[PDB]
Image (cartoon, rainbow, N blue to C red):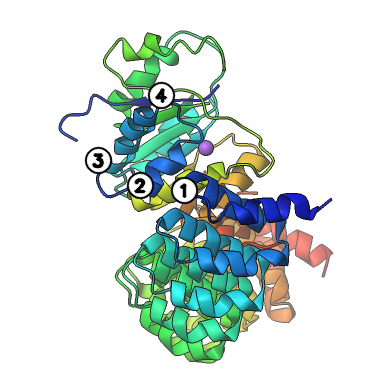
Amino acid sequence: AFLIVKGPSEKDNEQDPSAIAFLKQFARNHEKAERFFELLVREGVEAIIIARGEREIEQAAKLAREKGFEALAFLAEYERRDRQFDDIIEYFERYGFKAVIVAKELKQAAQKIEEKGFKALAFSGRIDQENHNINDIFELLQRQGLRAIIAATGLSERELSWAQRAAQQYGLDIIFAFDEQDNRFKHFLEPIRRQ
Amino acid sequence: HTDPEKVEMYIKNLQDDSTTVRFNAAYALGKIGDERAVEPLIKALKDEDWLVRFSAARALGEIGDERAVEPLIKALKDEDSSVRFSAAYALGKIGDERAVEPLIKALKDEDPRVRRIAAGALGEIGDERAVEPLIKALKDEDPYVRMAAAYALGKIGDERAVEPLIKALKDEDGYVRRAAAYALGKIGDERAVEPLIKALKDEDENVRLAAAQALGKIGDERAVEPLIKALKDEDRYVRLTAARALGKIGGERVRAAMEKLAETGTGFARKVAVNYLETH
Ligand code: NA
């Protein structure tokens, strides 16, 4: 699937046309993106946690809590298993996340989550042949404090490369948990990507 | 095929009145790289929307044409920090020496990522003109700039950075120390041996990891024994690195330190002493 979560919020368009414009490719309503644009601005998420599904998250959340970062979670997580979906909201309790993205294109029982006072969104999409650069969400998040990515354990060599490639192309750091030789800092050794 | 039907199609969408269609056409121009798109994106470097400027700047570095340098050079002074980053990133991807002095100015930017990427860009260009300004960026308050400046100073490999990087092995952040150690390893100066030896006693398991690999790159023998106690490191990879870094600094000094570890060594220190004394 593809779905993000949101904390209870409190007090929160401005001078920002290009940012909400980039949300329009994936976000549906024009005010849909407009509300999820203010998602990234207020808390100023400074860390993106990338994972798959569970003890991996407490490692990266510790690693997100390892640089004074107000992190934002992202992971695959496909099917149901008690809690999980229910514990999505507890990530904000346990780890103190500012938002959690979960990657079920249909069904999309988002009202299972937003019933208990947790704002949510909807789909986005995966592999695409250079129609719309999805990766620039890192750039909009970068302007909203995103100083580093943090890759939890278990990410495939593609998701590791994709997140490390996103670390290069957007001036973001990435923290691991190839991940043990010089490739742990490939985005810094090679700040500019290649062929 | 890289048919020009899609090429000139996105090209005409750069003057579209929709922001989304503009930068999404600029991104396709970068992924296509057809050089018939240099001038249209240079005009898009001043689009009223920053993302179209960001995407066109990035796409100009994706095509890799000399005609984008001076436009991106002016795009370094853009009002939007992301466009400043994208232009500094693209200039590093083009790597033309015209961008050195502008990126040296971008080393004095306000976005700690533009200065970070200007450092990384100046490292890719490798112009020795950028050495002294990068040394000033070893004092930038942002650690990612100090670290990117250190990485760029090591990629340039100019000896002028050795002692600035030597004093950067005592920086409060462990990532810039990771870079200063990796940098001094690439530069391979005998001056850095003693400070990297002291960096082997660092609290960070990554600074010890780099300082071990650095001294393996330097190939100096004053760090043979400091690498032996590094073979008793609590971090697994610092141990394996010192095993790699000692096979580099070959000779009898490492051999005589192996026969005393094939005899009286324990743990991982004995593990590689026998394997080295096997494969001399
Ligand atoms: Na994504």
Residue B159 is left or right of residue A193, and the answer is: left
> With respect to residue A109, does B73 lie above or below?
below
Circle 4 residues within 10 Å: few <14, some 14–19, many ≥20: many
Residue situated in front as seen by the camera: A73 or A122: A122
Q: Amino acid at mark 4?
A: Leu
Name which residue type carries label 1.
Thr
Real-space Cα distance between discs 4 and 1? 23 Å
Q: Does ligand 1 reach within 8 Å of label 1's beta carbon?
A: no
- Which marked residue is nearer to the observer: mark 1 or mark 3? 1
Amino acid type, mark 3: Arg
Alpha carbons under labels 3 and 4: distance apart: 17 Å
Residue beneath label 3, please?
A: A42
Callout 2: helix, strand or loop? Answer: helix
Q: Chain of mark 3?
A: A
Report the side of B62 relative to A41 (left or right).
Answer: right
Q: Which residue in the structure is indicated by mark 4? A: A121
